[PDB]
Image (cartoon, rainbow over all chains, first blue to last red; front, side):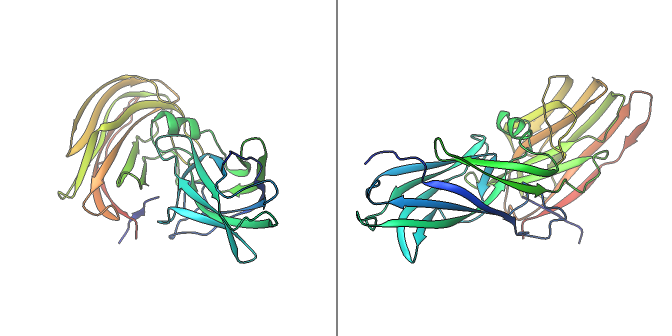
Length: 7
Length: 299
């Protein structure tokens, strides 16, 4: 799955 | 006792350990381990004296620990409490108390490691806009201070790998609030915007926008991490509810980009989906309507 990681 | 200064005396190393699978070594991508040299002398410090280490441009500590010890040659000589600046202030602090072990004949030299995330922006808050100017891609000097003694080190930071011309997003956890700030910047129309609609929403029922912590603005370009550097008023209308925040706007001048940000709450801040509205018409007539969804993860 394509996700974006938080910071 | 009293307030002392010059306990932290050197900035020995500043090294990145990728906390996830980040693609770039950015100041705001955790974790930066800052190793500082310190010294305490029982002839000039007593148990119960206090001292404070000021950390400009630091957003948070990337640990669940609330404090860290100053230890040398296996003995604890001070305890320091972490205070993250987050969205309250542009800097973080350590507030330290000398331990009873610092009996009068002790001369202690040691180091400590602090797990950090820098603030280089992320919303249109005063704090984030200020810190959006802290650093650039490449070599930077990072400076902390104890109250007189400035301690510095050079470090290399990588810019974001994301192409700044497209739409841009961000999600940063604010640990003391259990909220996440989230940002949306429209795709670039270099000659300005005739009009557009943008914003983001809860998708499945697990997300709530906090309408009391929002910003809507146009920024005069972006920094090396694709964050706003200014926030000016402009012609728009907005709707805001716990389900989402959306704007429709007109006549944004050349060189500016519209953006919206908000605090959000989620059932699980480590796994949530947002739905984005994304329509714009550049001055000159190029138009796109391209809504999308993003899956955000902290694991």
